[PDB]
Length: 68
Length: 75
Image (tube, rainbow over the protein chains, first blue to last red):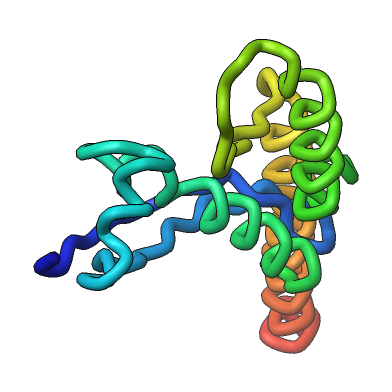
């Protein structure tokens, strides 16, 4: 239940379509009490599966609205 | 172009569509990622060429201004 980091690069498109390379740094940890469920639903290697989806989607989301 | 920019909801829609297409194979899903979106070469080269013209004709404006200094020095 200790903590663990992650980074996600994205070739996002700024508002003017400038394809900007932007990387985001994101931390995480699993909650102690609900480690049971987090293991049923994913398994031992839970974080590697989940970490980057939200980050890449949201780098695209945010930078689309923002200029290079 | 909007596949790049609007990728937030593009990914949301792809998530919904794959979730509805993939529920049939006796497996349980939690999250899915759409990471990359790239194009071959020409977009970035054209963007940089537009910036080339921008700053190059700014340099031409400064050649023009040294030509002004020329008017007078040569007067």
